[PDB]
Image (spheres, coloured by chain):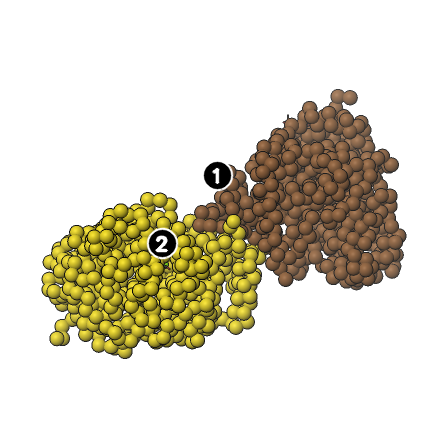
Chain colours: A brown, B yellow
Amino acid sequence: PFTMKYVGSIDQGTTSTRFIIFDERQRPVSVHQVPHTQHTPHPGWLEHDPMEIFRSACKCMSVAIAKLRQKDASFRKIEAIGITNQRETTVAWDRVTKEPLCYAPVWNDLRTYDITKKVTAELGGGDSMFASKITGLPVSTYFAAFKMRWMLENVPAVADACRRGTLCFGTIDTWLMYKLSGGKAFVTDVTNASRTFLMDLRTRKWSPELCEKLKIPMETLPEIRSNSELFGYVETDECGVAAALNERTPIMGSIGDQQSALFGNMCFEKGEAKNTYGTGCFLLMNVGEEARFSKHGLLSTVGFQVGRDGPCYYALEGAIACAGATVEWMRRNMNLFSHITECEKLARSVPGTQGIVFVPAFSGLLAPYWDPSARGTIVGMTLKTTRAHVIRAALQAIALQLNDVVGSMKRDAGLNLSSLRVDGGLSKNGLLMEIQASLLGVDILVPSMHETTALGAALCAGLAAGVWTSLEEVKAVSRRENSWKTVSPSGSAMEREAMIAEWREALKRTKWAK
Amino acid sequence: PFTMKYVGSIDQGTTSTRFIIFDERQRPVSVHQVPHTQHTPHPGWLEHDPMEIFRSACKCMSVAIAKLRQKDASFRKIEAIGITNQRETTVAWDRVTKEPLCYAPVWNDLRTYDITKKVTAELGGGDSMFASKITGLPVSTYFAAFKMRWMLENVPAVADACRRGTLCFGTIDTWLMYKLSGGKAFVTDVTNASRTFLMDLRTRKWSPELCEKLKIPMETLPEIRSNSELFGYVETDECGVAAALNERTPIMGSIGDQQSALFGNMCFEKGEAKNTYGTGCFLLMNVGEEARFSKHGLLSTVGFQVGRDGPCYYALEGAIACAGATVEWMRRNMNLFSHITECEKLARSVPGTQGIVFVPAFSGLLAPYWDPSARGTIVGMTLKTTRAHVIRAALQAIALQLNDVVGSMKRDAGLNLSSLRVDGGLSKNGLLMEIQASLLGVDILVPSMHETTALGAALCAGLAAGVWTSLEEVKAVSRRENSWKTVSPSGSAMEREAMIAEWREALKRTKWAK
Ligand SMILES: Nc1ncnc2c1ncn2[C@@H]1O[C@H](COP(=O)(O)OP(=O)(O)O)[C@@H](O)[C@H]1O
Ligand SMILES: Nc1ncnc2c1ncn2[C@@H]1O[C@H](COP(=O)(O)OP(=O)(O)O)[C@@H](O)[C@H]1O
Ligand SMILES: O=P(O)(O)OC[C@H](O)CO
Ligand SMILES: [Mg+2]
């Protein structure tokens, strides 16, 4: 009643794993990180060693716990652990060995492209969105199923293991939850399952039409649950993890990374949305207790579900391929600046782009204009154009794509974006947040506790273990402890429209590949 | 006589004047340069002070001569003087005062724009090319006639002097020979006269129809002579020039700057061309003894003429606005490199551009596809693209424009390109020269004695003075005494084809302004 309580969050990302311990204030009190290897066997491919990820996670936990006890020597244990992960990335493993059959292809890996084609033809009958009402997703290389298929066709040990009745497939939550539990648990959560291309969105249940249609035995699928409930206990002793925890610790949170950030930024109400700037962008809008579908090629997905049959919130999702990457490309590919802060400083040093548009579509346009053909392009240059204008044009362009994305989401959902919370690194660029607010015409909230993705999973775990009692208590503790900078709109109807008309014309000149 | 012979060359350019003394081996043995003031009363207006220009030339001659006397014991006198000049620039002066009535509008001056628009519509019925079978020229702000016309309409003293009959109009060649002369010569050479919009190419005589339509009296115009013959004698002693020359020195060569470079590069036979790679490019090809007109907006002009009523060689002329300028923008505006040596170093450091095209139409497209709407554009970029590729693409783009210019010339002229001689600062870029040889499929000759413009005028003078007796002897002395680096084609026709096909696609994306 006096001693502080803690919730652990495993944040398993594309390039590294972290364990963050939160206290009752929603403050990260201990953190450790461990990187894992980005295997690229052929151009366009990306693979991860699933045992390197498991071990990173256990290493992360034992180090973080150790540091925390130095800080609080009166702390016996963590209340619960939550998991949040890079989604779609699929592991295949043996039921008896408990070892992975092969490396895990990663959300953005392109090896499944041919399979993607075979699927669209032979099934959808050339319609990518054929199963969309069922799943929320267009046929794409990203989704699990198509990676499960590739492994079954192209990996000897995976094909064998299926016929023998020992094959377990799983997203990273599932893989982590399996190993952490000693092989005792085989579960996934609704957000992660919404990405398999094997789940029915409205019902949040596996679809026999698809597994069978896609030739994937149901036996290789884990049980689905909500994001906030008992999944299992931590029982493994890898890197002395169970001993560092002291008492058995339940895993009571599981949620995909983009949804975890929605939840960790308190986007509990429809119309609440978040954008995460990293190498790219991922914009998610909470749309309410009923699913919505897209006439603009956006993804329909689960936002969150707190508790077994607690209400389930749904969301729309969009993305931009190069955000941070564009900023870094200007630095390390083009020499336009050296120190990070020069980017903002140079773009502020000019009053606008004065003619030029820079469409930074280095790997094509996604969002509501799928076009793999589009490449990086600059138009309207004169001898007056400088690096300052080009940098400012890159930042405007990011904001312009997100404007387009939100325009679509509004119509596809028929709602107003009440506000946008942002996080990512690129959220540290004040000019970008200003441009973004003017174009969307809503407040942009920049939280100063910048561990919001990892907080999502801790909130799910802590809600189930009774650290926090309700979303209201969650919101209220957040207000008291974790401040945010708020960036309001400040444009003109005519300027906005002039930027957009100019941008629209530039887009027409970007088709290049093939 | 068998003592060393020396020929002098006044090179009167847009920003400076240089006097170069060549010996009989075509070696420049003394050089001096003096700038003149650039006056800009209104944007787009540029004007020169003709007296200042005259004085500079005189100063240049005496300093160059004095330097030579000091360093060469065998130098006694200059056999003859040749003059090469910035063309189109127009001097209005008074026959009795012997001084200018106003400053002289420069070739790139825009004040004649209204007049130009009026002329096309009023005498051209909206066709800018109406007079092009007579002049070889379109209606444009550059040509002398439109500057004369403008002075009469906006300069009271000129309109005044014109009335009294004391008016003298003249391009810089004419002005310099008059002053050097002491007022005893009122002459112009066929090449400069071809840039007035008042000469008939077929006859190489002033055109009454044109003078009447343009309303410039033919009394005000000087007499048209060849490039190489006796024009007059230096009789002034303005900067002690007469004192420095010592003996009587005849002025025996006069030729416009670009044509001078055609001559100094030995392009004596049809199909031989020169390109000057400076801020922009000026490509001229000798098309032979018969004028060739262009159905691609290329200019038809007089190439050269040795001797009074001697054979006259005609030329086609194209230009590109940004060449060296693009190199400078890349460094000054974009920070893509520091020392100009890095430009070629960085472009060499990648094997190609890997699908990007950089169209540097910063000030619109000229050449065979005039389009002032065009702007600087880059297409095809990916995250793998770097400054190295972008620098290389800029170089390719310069070579591709000239490839299209040459292409147009070949179709207009009905002849092949035999070889391309090169000069200008950017002809030091070895890779640019290699890309150009590979695109055109001809040898590129690079003079080590790079003062080609000054040499043209010195050869005209020296041919008329018997320092050299014929064009074959001129060619022999050049080959015997001065080194020519030869750059042979060294790509593949399949690469050529792809580069040209990407270039053509990119051009379509360049239209922006308005
Ligand atoms: N207001 C508080 N009430 C209770 N415990 C706290 C409080 N602030 C910090 N702690 C505990 O102190 C330890 C270190 O927290 P930390 O946030 O690093 O310290 P601080 O915020 O004072 O810089 C953690 O155990 C944290 O739970
Ligand atoms: N060593 C070099 N390597 C590459 N480019 C050069 C080098 N020297 C000069 N340049 C470029 O070539 C141009 C030279 O132009 P120049 O011929 O002197 O003037 P103009 O174009 O008026 O004749 C400059 O703009 C410069 O950018
Ligand atoms: O030859 P310049 O450098 O005087 O330039 C004049 C050109 O003819 C313009 O087209
Ligand atoms: Mg030039």
Q: Residue at x 51, y 61 (%)?
A: B350
Q: Residue at x 62, y 59 (%)?
A: A513
Spot occupied by residue B93 in the image (x, y as percentages of width and height): 22, 53
For residue B417, above or below residue A311: below
The residue that label 2 is drawn on is B108
What whole-number distance in Å separates the C-alpha atoms at marks 1 and 2? Answer: 32 Å
Q: Residue at x 76, y 52 (%)?
A: A138
- Report the mark closest to the observer, 1 or 2: 2
Check whether the beta carbons of the residues at disc 1 and disc 2 lie within 8 A of each other. Answer: no
- Residue B44 located left or right of residue A365: left
- Residue A309 located left or right of residue A343: right
Mark 2 Cα within 10 Å, few/some/many (few <14, many 20+)?
Answer: some
Q: Is mark 1 on a helix, strand or loop?
A: loop
Residue A349, numbered label: 1
Q: What residue type is labelled 1?
A: Ser
Spot occupied by residue B478 in the image (x, y as percentages of width and height): 28, 73
Q: Does the residue labelled 2 lie within 8 Å of ligand 3?
A: yes
Q: Which of B99 and B350 is in front in this view?
A: B99
